[PDB]
Amino acid sequence: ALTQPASVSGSPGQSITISCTGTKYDVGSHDLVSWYQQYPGKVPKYMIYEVNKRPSGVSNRFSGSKSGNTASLTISGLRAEDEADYYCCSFGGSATVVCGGGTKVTVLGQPKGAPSVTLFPPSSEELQANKATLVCLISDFYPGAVTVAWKADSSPVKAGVETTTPSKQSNNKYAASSYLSLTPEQWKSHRSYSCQVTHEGSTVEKTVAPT
Amino acid sequence: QVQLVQSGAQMKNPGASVKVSCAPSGYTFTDFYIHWLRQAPGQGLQWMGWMNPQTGRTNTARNFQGRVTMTRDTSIGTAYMELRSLTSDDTAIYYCTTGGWISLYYDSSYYPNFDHWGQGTLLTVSGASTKGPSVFPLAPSSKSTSGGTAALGCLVKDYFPEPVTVSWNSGALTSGVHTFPAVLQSSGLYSLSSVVTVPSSSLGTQTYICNVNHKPSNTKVDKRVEPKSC
Image 1 (cartoon, rainbow over the protein chains, first blue to last red):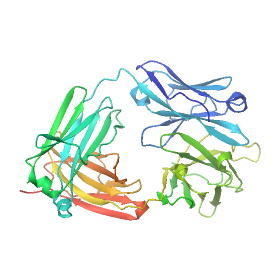
Image 2 (cartoon, one colour):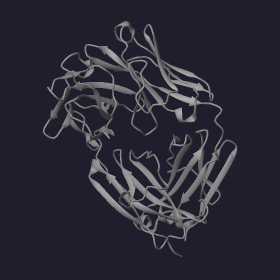
Image 3 (cartoon, rainbow over the protein chains, first blue to last red):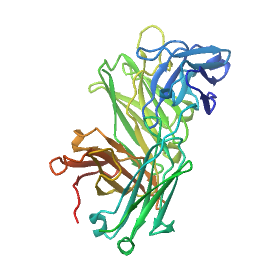
Image 4 (cartoon, rainbow over the protein chains, first blue to last red):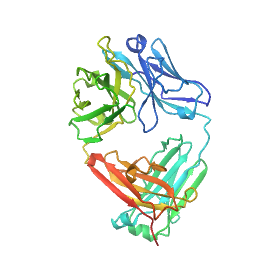
């Protein structure tokens, strides 16, 4: 496996380079290295091939190079749209291909987004199936770090909460979700249940009550 | 206009075998090499093998040399990958791609030139049992949305393994749809939500149905979502 750095950070407008180091028998003695782009949840995209060449449709801001046993992918005029995982693939000997571990590109100087929070109460249908689930949906926040807490009336609930780790949205922001699992009796017994979402010093508290 | 269509998601017990299909279209099947790669969660691309659609000749990577078999059906233009002796290490998304141009002169089988990719095939290899989903409607809430607009959705609860896909009105509704990543619960089962922002004025007259597809367990659910009352 070719060696790539885990992450590479850069400010907008700057020019950044991702390395890909193999041996002499692969990337050392052959100009047969391609680069691919992958947005979270999506399929890889042809970016560079044969070290230097660009496929049609690919932005001219992407350029490849090679020295000794190392390939490099260079992005100029850095944008948020370039935030992704980038992979290099090279000829590996005996008519094989070898791939690199990939590299996450982070674009600094990126500002801040406040989370949007939507709280759904259990459905009459789930309630009839003798179950209850509160659904908290958090989205469009940046950076991708958030703490979610649940409350019964005004005292904390930790039992049966199951919260996701933030995941990169398509608009370079983040989404997450939290799920409070409950019994119908519990749902009915209380004045309210709350999902409070804390994101960089600020807190949004959404609250639902039984009908 | 080139599109590579892979088979659907699969669940397999450890030690079994799996066969994934890929049907490329928009070009001549026997003009380009087919490559097979995979992505294990947390990791990155792993090249598995290549196949010549014209002659049928295949070459595999070293770590897969006994376990993989790539074949083709030239009559329908479909490549196949068979992987055997499955373990948790084979749990990954499997891709088939197009390689170089096939020529009588010069070998381009090993050119890492993958222009076109399949949509992916998620394999989960586990001794656990396949769990189908329960689907519940999330009634419209205007409380936290933008102007004369409300938010409704679907809760896809307690299934295994990944993945499920959600559409709306049989694919007719794509605007304002956010299908969230699933949570892995301590029960070992997955749950996700799909939420749509729709106009408030059109409620009562517009129909909202979520189409939940969980191919590993062979379940389709069409859930109608309508406002509540009190």
